[PDB]
């Protein structure tokens, strides 16, 4: 492994970022 | 490492999947 951790660490943070948006988008849709 | 491509594969899947869901969501939320 040369940059697996770096790529993985980015994939997680990047994925979690989209997850946070999914909640906000769903919240506005659910709330209204 | 263990699951290099495995974890990366799941990351991309979960990612690209999130953007696809958020896309259709926002696209619908923007109109409403």
Image (spheres, helix red, strand yellow):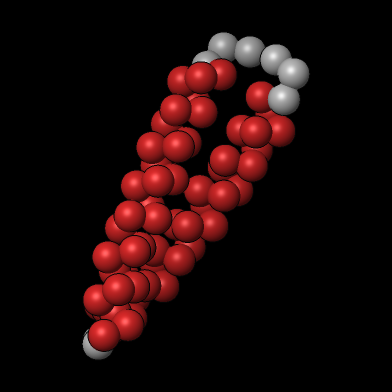
The answer to whether residue A25 is left or right of residue A18 is left
Residue B19 % position (x, y)? 39, 55
Residue closest to the far top? B2
The quadrant holding residue A3 is top right
**Image: A7 above or below A29:** above
Q: Residue at x 41, y 73 (%)?
A: A24
**Image: B5 above or below B16:** above
- Give A23 or B27, whichever is nearer the viewer: B27
The quadrant holding residue A32 is bottom left
Q: Which quadrant does the C terminus of chain B fall into?
A: bottom left
Q: Residue at x 63, y 13 (%)?
A: B1
Q: Residue at x 51, y 28 (%)?
A: B8
Q: Residue at x 57, y 40 (%)?
A: A11
- Give A21 or B12, whichever is nearer the viewer: B12
The answer to whether residue B25 is left or right of residue B19 is left
Residue B9 % position (x, y)? 44, 28
Residue B26 % position (x, y)? 34, 73
**Image: A14 above or below B23:** above
The answer to whether residue A6 is left or right of residue A13 is right
- The count of marks equals 0
Residue B16 % position (x, y)? 40, 46
């Amino acid at each position: 492994c040369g940059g697996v951790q770096a790529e993985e660490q980015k994939l997680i943070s990047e994925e979690d970022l989209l997850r946070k948006r999914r909640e906000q988008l769903k919240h506005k849709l659910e709330q209204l | 490492c263990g699951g290099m491509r495995r974890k990366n594969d799941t990351h991309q899947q979960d990612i690209d999947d999130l953007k696809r869901q958020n896309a259709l969501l926002e696209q619908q939320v923007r109109a409403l």
